[PDB]
Length: 459
Ligand SMILES: CC(=O)N(C)c1ccccc1C(=O)O
Ligand SMILES: [Zn+2]
Ligand SMILES: [Zn+2]
Ligand SMILES: [Zn+2]
Image 1: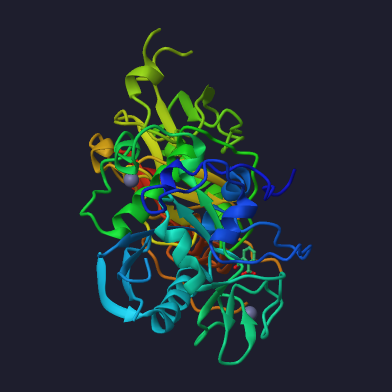
Image 2 (image 1 turned 180 degrees about the vertical axis):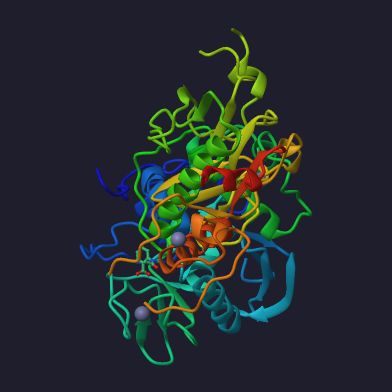
């Protein structure tokens, strides 16, 4: 069972206000037919427009909440809302657009999905809290058929053009008018009691309800993210490489080693309490320090309370030496800390909008991260950029312009002139650091941290 059987039952109770008289006994096969689409017994990679929760989780980057609200059923205008915040009014003749016929509305739908999704996914998953009008409006902007490739590249087709009779992916679809072979999922099939607003507001206070279709579309995708990534966590699902994943992760390991090594050299802590990932390894294996590990999986709901991590009776004395919290999200860090905290507000192709201010960070695996909170860092300060190295000054084996920097902490810079090797190493470390920061990671340290204490390690 890889795909969702068209003969699976679909509960129609949520559809009966917009569709009175709808049969209680309904399959996906019959629903797709009621929506005006013919599947023709096609074994060509598109077995059903609807997908399983497991297939939806694997394709979370394609999620687009979609809701349709009647403004006044072929006679009345419809308000089409998307989790991008867009509201389009389609006439059958927070961005609110005036009423227009379907022939122009569909062009706008293709442009919007193509721009939102081209750098995220190879498809679209319409995330619904289905009541009827959204399912019956699909025939006005969606075409289905066999799986196809783009006319201009090797990617799968996501759009169709009636003007040219061709197919395109999200990257080559300018001027295309139809969404081709989209996927969709109805959250209301997961067994909920009560309406969308009541279930969404149980877990989220960041998204409100003005009463427009995009507010519902946003709430729908948020509730789906809460169910699939907050209350249920799956770190075994792998996600494709769409950007700088490898470089960011490599940069994070470089910055961690640099920052921890320098903290140990500058303040000579006898003990380090490493709180976080139970699979963590010593980031400074040669350091003299007593390294003690404490297990805490990435929190996906609320940040950990420091009282629960440290108290209830371990070294017991977390106040001795230094605490290292590398992506271990806590409510209030102790003063003796070295911290890497992902800033959920960051705009990138890796970071998707999440639940209750949190974000869904997708890099190899999916990690719902609780909302960034500046008050967690009141006992610390922002860690300044610096490069430290005790390695010999020797080139071995790309061109050169002399480096002058007060933040290149090396024997050669103490001696008045940065050597070529430390200049190359400094520029590469500065690049890794900038990549990490721009990806969304923030670095914080104990107030007494001073890089001036690193110069005396060259005696
Ligand atoms: C690699 C990349 O940038 N993206 C968005 C993709 C991700 C999964 C499948 C296909 C694609 C594609 O568009 O090729
Ligand atoms: Zn293409
Ligand atoms: Zn929400
Ligand atoms: Zn040097």
